[PDB]
Image (tube, rainbow, N blue to C red):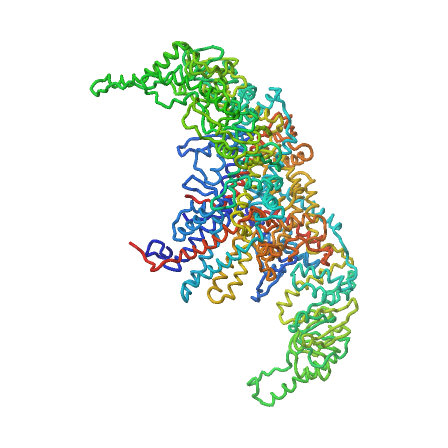
Amino acid sequence: NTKRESGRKVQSGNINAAKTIADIIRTCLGPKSMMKMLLDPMGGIVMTNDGNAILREIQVQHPAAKSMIEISRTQDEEVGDGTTSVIILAGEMLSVAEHFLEQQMHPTVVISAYRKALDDMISTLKKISIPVDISDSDMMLNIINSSITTKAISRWSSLACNIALDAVKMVQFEENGRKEIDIKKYARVEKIPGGIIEDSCVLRGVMINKDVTHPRMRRYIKNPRIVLLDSSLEYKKGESQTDIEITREEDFTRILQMEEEYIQQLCEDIIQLKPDVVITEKGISDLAQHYLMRANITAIRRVRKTDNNRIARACGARIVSRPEELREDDVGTGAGLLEIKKIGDEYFTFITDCKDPKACTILLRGASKEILSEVERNLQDAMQVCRNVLLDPQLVPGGGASEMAVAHALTEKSKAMTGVEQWPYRAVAQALEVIPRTLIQNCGASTIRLLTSLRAKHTQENCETWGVNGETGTLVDMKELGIWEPLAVKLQTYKTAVETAVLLLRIDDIVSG
Amino acid sequence: MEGPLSVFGDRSTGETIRSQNVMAAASIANIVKSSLGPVGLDKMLVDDIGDVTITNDGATILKLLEVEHPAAKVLCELADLQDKEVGDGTTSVVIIAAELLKNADELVKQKIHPTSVISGYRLACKEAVRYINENLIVNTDELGRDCLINAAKTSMSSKIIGINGDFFANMVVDAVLAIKYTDIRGQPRYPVNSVNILKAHGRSQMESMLISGYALNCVVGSQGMPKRIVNAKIACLDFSLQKTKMKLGVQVVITDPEKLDQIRQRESDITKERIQKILATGANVILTTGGIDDMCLKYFVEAGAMAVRRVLKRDLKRIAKASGATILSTLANLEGEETFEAAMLGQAEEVVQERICDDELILIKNTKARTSASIILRGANDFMCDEMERSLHDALCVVKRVLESKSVVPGGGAVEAALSIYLENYATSMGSREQLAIAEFARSLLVIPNTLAVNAAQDSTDLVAKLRAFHNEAQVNPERKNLKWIGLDLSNGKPRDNKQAGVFEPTIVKVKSLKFATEAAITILRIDDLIKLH
Amino acid sequence: MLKEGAKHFSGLEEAVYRNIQACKELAQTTRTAYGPNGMNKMVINHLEKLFVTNDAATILRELEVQHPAAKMIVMASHMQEQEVGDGTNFVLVFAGALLELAEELLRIGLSVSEVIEGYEIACRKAHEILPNLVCCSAKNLRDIDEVSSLLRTSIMSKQYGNEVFLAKLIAQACVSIFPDSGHFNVDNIRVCKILGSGISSSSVLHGMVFKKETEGDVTSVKDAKIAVYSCPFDGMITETKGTVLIKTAEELMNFSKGEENLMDAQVKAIADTGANVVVTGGKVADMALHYANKYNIMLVRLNSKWDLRRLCKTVGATALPRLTPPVLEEMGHCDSVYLSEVGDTQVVVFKHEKEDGAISTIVLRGSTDNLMDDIERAVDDGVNTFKVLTRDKRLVPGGGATEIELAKQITSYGETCPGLEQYAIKKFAEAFEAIPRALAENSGVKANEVISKLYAVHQEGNKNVGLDIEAEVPAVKDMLEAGILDTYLGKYWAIKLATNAAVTVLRVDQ
């Protein structure tokens, strides 16, 4: 309707949410790890190192709290992790500068500061980003188990990283998009219930769990050939329209029978032609696929073009109307293996597909069905490191001095870059030093003076590579600490965070409706 | 509705509701004053409950804004009028009226007769329009010294993409002249989106390159089919090839699959015959609308053919009239045995395909039917190009808008800071009520620059000093020359040296909102016999 | 406390929160009260007397605070003003500003001694580079423009407008007339306001200016044996009788007749005690006066205790009620004792001026005392801003230019030093911008503009601000190079004295 709002009132409510968002997770983030509990209206506890959980589960505070879960999922998609980082970084960067600078009163000179610190981030990152080799799955393994240990898991760090190493390489887009930026669709993650890591097979390709649902279907055939419709399924999907009588019990049934009988004869047209796979993208019927499974023809049914398309190239299956009808072939082998591997009686067909676009659905195994999810998450952010290190072998040592690594270089440029912008630049110079100091405040001692000594150690000795240990609070080498921080993650979390701050800096009025 | 209320329907009964309306209306008008300009702070504005719009465009917001007042009705109305009118002044028309509806009605009852009151705005709404249209003094894409290049540069210079005003200054000069679309009624203006504007994250920010003819966009990475022959000619086709279904549209309900499967076997061969028969009439590069499926993308590449498919029809259309091909002449039905002729041959000097930056196109070189041109942007990243492209677009539309108006008046309130005084002077000597009124007009012309630069944190006194430090008694004249700089950079918020830039608005978008905003002061007045219905 | 017990009004919130704010509001008042300003602060006395001043102690003296926080410190600005002129209006605000950084450090959770010392540490560091900030010194205390350059500052440090001719007339008052070698006298230099004429018409009469009416014939001799008396004539008659007029009637005609020659006796005994001028804190007696006109004894019909004070002070006088033939105790000092008309009022004048007993008494003409008072406020300071009692004052930049100089310096060191000590030493060099923020307001600009440039001017010992348009955009004045300078001395004091309390006032939670 007719409405207007003002400035700091709308600006502080940002921080009011943004701060609380930033709060408990910074004790949860890093080696120091805490539970963010929610009391349900239902009365239940929900205990997380993740904010989005407790956030989503509860009343949404409109300006800030609605903004960050988005940029969280923005960030959660980017490298796979760092929602916690973005949401705390922004609110952090949104706090001390603003009112200070907004009592000095200006949006814009603050805005340019977001970039410069984000730029002062970039350079000294990629300056102090330590190249770690992808030629070594080791120099991936050292950094890949490093980012699977982020909070609570040193356990699945061993297995899930193993699965992630060459998978990321094996992960491909279908453009030959490389594969360093690779997504978790082309990395695809499906945890397979039951089994164990001893049962774990390394699937660097995709599992098609549609492939073998029953032993009747083709199994342990090196590479399939997927015949898509068009001839081997001739075209009648219909029915002969027999009469109906509400009196008889049988007349309701016989009409539905005549609908499936034609695909039954389409799947019969398949038997003689003898594919090993028939992909039916329109699909088949219930009694029809029995006919399919007669000839040892596995049916991939009601499946999209692209699942087949990727799998076809992945599984090395041609694309044809009919084995006696020739446009020739798509691919005979994209897959150096076809594995049909079952836990329970449902066959999960795991087909390792070399550098294929595929899904790269990578077989992961927990000690049970449930902890597979964390393994997957341990496998996800393990791919994060790989895709990071495949992207940039440069990444930064960590344990938190990376967050200082910008912070004091800012202090120098506040005195160097200057202008009146130094004041935003100096006011944003402060934001990056609370987070490690919080890890060290979780340690206590003097988390303050240590950080000043770190701030010394920053310019004195090392900005990040020789850092502070988060669970300790001593001067440490973040390389020798062995905690490695992906370079791109820094490029992501900070960037993503400054923007919602610029965002919630930009909007001083929110009308409802 | 204020005080103890014995009546409904926005009755505060007179000055109260008048004030309450000027309370109402201005309470809307304030969103713009901060939102004025892109540096004008955006507002995250819930559309329903959880649906938030982020907009600094006022009349765009005023469409989100819902009308609970007669004041709320008309400002949304009149700004949405100006909105659909242009889009330049959506914000702007909203600001001053809140004062203009705070002013004249006070005089309208001070009427000897009510008419002379608003005319103090009106002939001033003229007196400015005169002075406005008199302004070539800033905002010149009509001429630079190198003509449009420097003006496009001054545009690009008033912007930053990074390094600009170099190939982009030139690029703006191409874009309009690259467009032979003759806008109706003899308009010497060329739609700037009719340009084929292509982009490369490769090379350099400053770098951009014009292409002979309209550059056809041929799908990249998706063709195992040959698109490439170097010849003078092309065949632009509106047409497509599908082996899965071309002759087959019919349902599967047919009792026998026999018909569908057998023509299905015939569908593939003629798609191999069709390409050759568009090849055999003298077109080896044959530009076909294409759009083949995913598993059908398998069927052609495995079986084989040559056709250029899945091309942008916008280009293919532009390339069609460019080179002189015909997308449709004898083509109606879908088939591979369909007849084909030479009337579909596009005429270029050569037809070449150049890959650069890791991007390749089908280049129709010197299209013989119409002069055609496409500039391909070069960024450091895909980011850089949206910067150059739109910084260009600043000049581009203005260049066309200067093709729309020779009179092109300074962007920014520095046009008003003059008008806020000259007409403030044009108030006194007028005498009586329009003396009262013309000042109310002019003195309120001051508010746009204040707010805008406040939005850019260039604020008021400085700006309004600088603006009217230029204008003097010695400088009363729009002129073209600046010892009075009547220009104001919108993005800077501070008046600057850009006299040529495409960040300034022509007199088109200007003279209106004067008429618009005062109407709002008029529009609210109109009541006779205030009443209530029950 | 939790209990019924003990005595405290500070501590907990108060120490941290409320004392700092008690350490705030008045500093907040003093911010444009110091330095070049157009700020003005109205005040009413216990007289309910409407007056305006940017001087603190005037305002201060009538301010009561339950806390010692605001209370105790003001002595320092006085302890300061005990030493010098203004800079006093700077003293407290320097503290209050740098203080509230600590409550932030208290939010940041820094320990008292941790907060305490870095200032104290850097308080040296200030005093250490403070001499490096000596850009000049005081050459001729006899010269007007040598001195007027300074005097303009405390006046400026008081108020912006009137500073110049003041700084002139005060050296035209001849602060010259003393060596100021360690010998300087503001008892021999007095500001005596004539209500009348203008303040540009305000003069300085060297020799005591008493606007009090010179009563009857002037001094017997100019080396005046002076009889200063609180009540030299209370009347010699008592009329109490049958009617307290007449009952036995002729008994009346005795005393009204016998009274006056006792006033003659006293006045003759003023001539007999030897006073070349008699001085009445009490009334004049007309016959006595007439006798004192016969005896040609200069007289003052009525004498302020202030009069009598300076009278008793400098003459060696003793103001006494006398119903007796008088006794010289008071005797003389001043070797020329005159009548002047300045603003055209009888001015009782006493001048012995020896360059040591040297009396240069500023005589302010003006049509308003409140005028001549807020004037005299800055005039109070200029003379004793001039009063360093170093003939060479090691002139340092006026107006606050030295501030930013050490803002860079000592926080750059504050950078270098480690630990929690840092911000202690770091906040220290941040204490400057307060007034560069404060006067920047009355100047009309934000302090970032000011300070970024006051930083970007870097080491100057000139470039600075105040109430000016130079103080607006440029963040540049000449607070050295224009003739606005400061003695090295009060600097050390304005620095040190406030640093002590700011440290100390927090440490007490009681």
Q: Relative to residue B396, is residue A339 depicted above or below?
A: above
Measured as percent of width and height from the top left, residue A212 is found at: 43, 14
Q: Relative to residue B224, is residue B10 depicted above or below?
A: below
- Is A319 in front, or is A41? A319
* Left or right of C230 on screen, residue A351: left
- Is B450 in front, or is A65? B450
Q: Residue at x 67, y 60 (%)?
A: C156
Measured as percent of width and height from the top left, residue A498 is found at: 55, 38
Measured as percent of width and height from the top left, residue A313 is found at: 50, 18
The part of the image, by quadrant, that contains residue B106 is bottom left
Measured as percent of width and height from the top left, residue A125 is found at: 63, 32
The part of the image, by quadrant, that contains residue A111 is top right
- Is B475 in front, or is C43? B475
Quadrant of the snapshot with the C terminus of chain A: top left
Q: Residue at x 38, y 60 (%)?
A: B14
Toward the left, the furthest residue is A247
Q: Is residue C12 visible?
A: no
Q: Is residue A4 visible?
A: yes
Q: Relative to residue A19, is residue B341 depicted above or below?
A: above
Q: Residue at x 70, y 74 (%)?
A: C228
